[PDB]
Length: 5
Length: 271
Ligand SMILES: CN1CCN(c2ccc(-c3cnc4[nH]cc(NC(=O)c5cccnc5)c4c3)cc2)CC1
Image 1: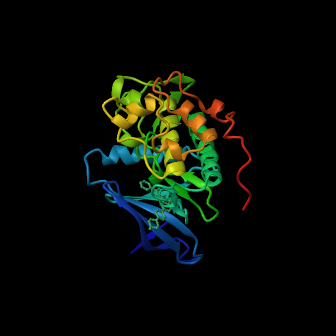
Image 2: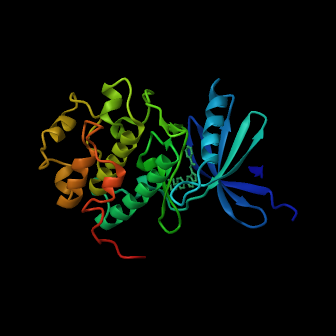
């Protein structure tokens, strides 16, 4: 799992 | 700098009907932040609710409040980037039926008052203070978290009385169970007094502050030879006697808690 800023 | 906006989600910090909070580590810098993830599709009003919580978080900037860095929407999902507190929850530093060393409780209580004074100073009440929501950083500094129930009680120098029944029963003030409207500030002062009781005794004094609850009646009748009170030394117990007062208008305010004898007793050595 990942997310962008 | 390529990739500096990429964050890997590496650990579940918390979960609940509100959604989840994950530990996010920057792909490039390895900076760690917590990311609260909310699915606005879970409830019809989640949209307005989370929007309110972001609005409130944007107003806050204090060392004893979980800092809010910004947010990003992705369709129906909202991502809130928040200060990561590596020491976890104050909840987990409270030993069952023991509590924690009094000087440690005093230092956490000072830090909690600082954050609550800050919030009330800008007109925000938290409405659900308890150990599960008071987080600790790498140096054991306390930071108030979760503004999902927070609301404005003062705006343009005018106070709005509250009427919403909310919070958590063992920590909630008695006036929410007996009165239609109430001032906000004394309710947060009350939950801070139950948090102090838990830190010094490792147990909550009552299921709820109603006469029907034997433990609450016993307190009103000053039976302090019973637990949790018998486990608390006299100086902090004198402070709890001023905070856990049923009438919110007679209850001690924070400026007077700051002048309390126990509050000012030198007890805790620096790290
Ligand atoms: C045993 N194990 C138990 C858990 N511990 C544990 C360790 C770290 C954290 C933790 C750390 N940093 C945080 N920043 C913001 C948080 N939460 C929020 O902002 C927030 C939370 C709910 C609703 N709304 C907002 C948050 C929670 C929690 C538990 C680690 C050890």
